[PDB]
Image 1 (cartoon, helix red, strand yellow):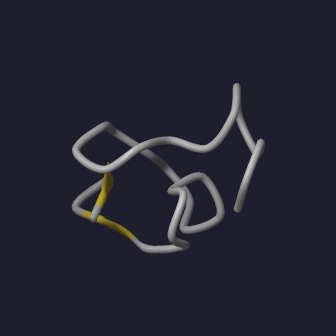
Image 2 (cartoon, one colour):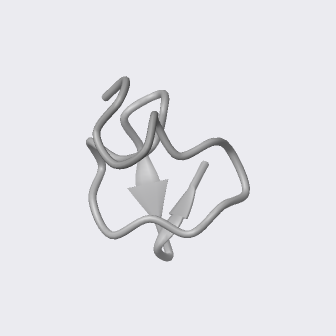
Length: 32
């Protein structure tokens, strides 16, 4: 979640894990 890969990955940015995205949802490799 928070601070998983240089902080959490904010909405609209690419992620490769649900834990990367700040609100725990990564879809299409982007933080929803």
